[PDB]
Image (cartoon, coloured by chain):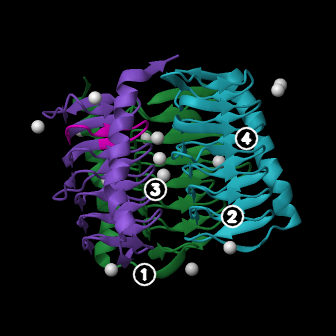
Chain colours: A purple, B cyan, C green
Amino acid sequence: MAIYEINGKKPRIHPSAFVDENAVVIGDVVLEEKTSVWPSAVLRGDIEQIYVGKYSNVQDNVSIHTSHGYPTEIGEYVTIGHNAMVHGAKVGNYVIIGISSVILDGAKIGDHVIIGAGAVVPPNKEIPDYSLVLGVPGKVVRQLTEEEIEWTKKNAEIYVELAEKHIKGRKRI
Amino acid sequence: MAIYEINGKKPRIHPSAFVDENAVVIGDVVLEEKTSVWPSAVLRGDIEQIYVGKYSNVQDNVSIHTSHGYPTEIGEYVTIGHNAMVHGAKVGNYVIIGISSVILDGAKIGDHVIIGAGAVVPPNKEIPDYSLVLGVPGKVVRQLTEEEIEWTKKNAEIYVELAEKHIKGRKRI
Amino acid sequence: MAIYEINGKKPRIHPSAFVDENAVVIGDVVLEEKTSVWPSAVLRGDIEQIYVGKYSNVQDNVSIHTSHGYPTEIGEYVTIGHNAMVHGAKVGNYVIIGISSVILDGAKIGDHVIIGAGAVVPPNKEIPDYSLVLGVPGKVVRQLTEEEIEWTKKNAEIYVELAEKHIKGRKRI
Ligand SMILES: [Ca+2]
Ligand SMILES: [Ca+2]
Ligand SMILES: [Ca+2]
Ligand SMILES: [Ca+2]
Ligand SMILES: [Ca+2]
Ligand SMILES: [Ca+2]
Ligand SMILES: [Ca+2]
Ligand SMILES: [Ca+2]
Ligand SMILES: [Cl-]
Ligand SMILES: [Cl-]
Ligand SMILES: [Cl-]
Ligand SMILES: [Zn+2]
Ligand SMILES: [Zn+2]
Ligand SMILES: [Zn+2]
């Protein structure tokens, strides 16, 4: 994307990662292998670090930030849905963060979790593995089905391929 | 906006359309006559096509995407509110998509419909004509009034004029 | 940010304000001393004026707009959270607009108010001072605590310092 350093920090971006030139990555941000950051997404690492694990995607118009003492750590095969916002939270592996949802400071999202579109996970809220979270404040309404569990990985894999397609075939006109 | 092709697809944009240079239009996207795409809006046509009918506007920080087998088709005189997100859905004519609302895959929004701000239309949800939709999950709470019906067109017309004003009078400083 | 005039209006920006180059400021917009506009934020002053008072911040992916007869006026020490949207509303001093929340036309937000993440303040809704607002439609659920009241200022002060850090230490790479 448009990539920036701020005072002593430069983003650490794996060569295989896709960062749309219209995305904004600033400071203390780590993007691992096969990650992807889409148009208009903002990863502002000007306070605590923002870490994005392997095979994870940060979709269009998403914002990721932190609070003092609350870094944002994202696991592997994580899908951060369009227009969602993650703030100073810990997100496990195989997690689908719903479109336009919000994850607040201190929250701990387990593995194989789906956060519904528009849901808001309150500060310090701990979400167990295999949970479906809906509402504002977000509640665990039930456990995921086998189909949804397979989807928590599939969604991310689709993006890994999409990222490569953009890396190789995008052309500004 | 910042316009891009991806592998064999180039956006088809009508000469009268306004696409803010800060918007992002990629791939298989069709923008008809008198449409407008505002700052920070993202129309990513990298899977299925995104079609935007005549006199329709896609406001600031909006994201439009699709899923395999689920293209996004927008009708005429449609207002896609600031920060809203439309994903693989069919939207009819004279529809006001509320600010920061979400329309999910397979949804079919009828004509002369108003989706409230922050509402979430679930996947495959069918919304009848003349409906007011509120909530998460979005429910049809009542039919529109005559004033609201006239507004479903007026809102779009205001934007058609606004688009022309920007086309002719915008200047970067 | 990317700054623009539209027909006779040029933004009035105080020398001390920070406007990220990835933000979009258009037309009739006033940004006072020590204000800050972050990446992907959009302040579109193409209808009525958008005024942002001293020490206030407009975070990443936020959109601010107006309606005919409804300008947007923001007071001092106001924090407009990531991905929030303010439309033709009046916001007082020491107000925290929650992440991904929505403030609609004609709304009047009092001083020392916290709007919860994802909440939607309905058109013409008046929120009294020292209120905590939650829900859709947004309701005053209780008065703020002393800690929250001190936070309504602290949040903004953190940003004033952050803005200066970016003004002096940002570097594109
Ligand atoms: Ca390695
Ligand atoms: Ca944006
Ligand atoms: Ca948003
Ligand atoms: Ca390969
Ligand atoms: Ca024609
Ligand atoms: Ca004309
Ligand atoms: Ca002064
Ligand atoms: Ca100083
Ligand atoms: Cl729970
Ligand atoms: Cl219904
Ligand atoms: Cl109330
Ligand atoms: Zn923040
Ligand atoms: Zn998508
Ligand atoms: Zn508007």
Cα separation between marks 1 and 2: 40 Å
Q: Are marks 3 and 4 in contact (CB under 8 Å)?
A: no
Cα separation between marks 3 and 2: 19 Å
- In the image, taking residue B46 as reference, residue A59 lies left or right, namely left
Cα separation between marks 1 and 4: 42 Å
Front in this rendered view, residue B123 or C173: B123
Q: Are marks 1 and 4 in contact (CB under 8 Å)?
A: no
Q: Secondary structure at mark 4?
A: loop
Front in this rendered view, residue A75 or C148: A75
Give amino acid for label 3: Ile
Query: How many residues crowd mark 3 within 10 Å: few (<14), some (14–19), many (20+)?
Result: many
Question: Above or below — where is B71 with respect to C3?
Answer: below
Quadrant position of residue C104: bottom right
Ligand 4 quadrant assignment? top left
Cα separation between marks 3 and 1: 31 Å
Indicate which label's residue lies in the foreground, 3 or 2. 2
Q: Which residue is mark 2?
A: B126
Q: Secondary structure at mark 2?
A: strand
Instruction: Inspect the magenta stretch and tell me whether residue C1 lies in it.
Output: no
Give amino acid for label 2: Glu
In the image, farthest residue toward the right: B146
Give amino acid for label 1: Gln
Quadrant position of residue B143: bottom right
Q: Which residue is mark 3?
A: A99
Query: How many residues crowd mark 1 within 10 Å: few (<14), some (14–19), many (20+)?
Result: some
Q: Chain of mark 1?
A: C
Q: Secondary structure at mark 3?
A: loop
Q: Which residue is mark 1?
A: C143
Q: Which residue is mark 4?
A: B56
- In the image, taking residue C146 as reference, residue B156 lies left or right, namely right
Give, as a single range, the part of the protein colored magenta.
Answer: A29-43
